Image (cartoon, rainbow, N blue to C red; front, side, top):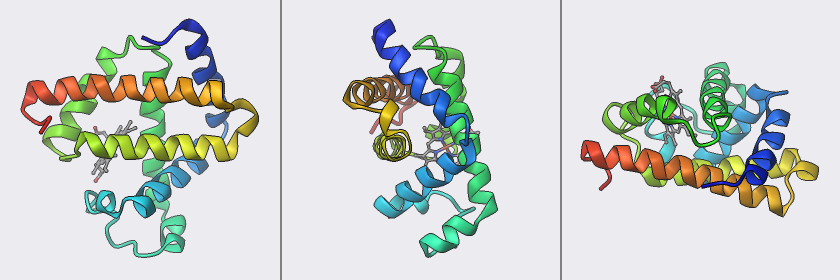
Length: 153
Ligand code: HEM
């Protein structure tokens, strides 16, 4: 359970992200795919991209980055009361996209790296710790739905 003070830190940096959703989403997916190449293989849509320059040039990758960050933003702004938003996401990522919880850890590390790069004055250690807690709460709740469905592994 995050405290109100921890949520305020999370949402204050998140408000900065919402000024350039697409730029952040590109940086976060490119970092995920470079750091953890197994993740790129889950996207039939992107598995043709072989270089960071090709990733940066892909408008369809930039579009998906916006989709991802808009869904994450809607979850964060619920401050934990996010059951309605997580249900469908867990369901599609377990049963259709086949994404292991570990890959949600990896994309959480990529988000935190990008926020620190782009927003260092609003992403000191207090805020990094709070964002880490928010993203762990996301993963915990998705993992419980995966387990329900037979995918926690
Ligand atoms: C913060 C974490 C994430 C969020 C909020 C998120 C969000 C979304 C949303 C909103 C969609 C489209 C609606 C749907 O299918 O449910 C989607 C699609 C998808 N996601 Fe995620 N996602 C996340 C992490 C991941 C990770 C880590 C992977 C792979 C490693 C992944 C793989 C996919 C795939 C393969 C699709 C379908 C893309 C396509 O072919 O159109 N997601 N995601």
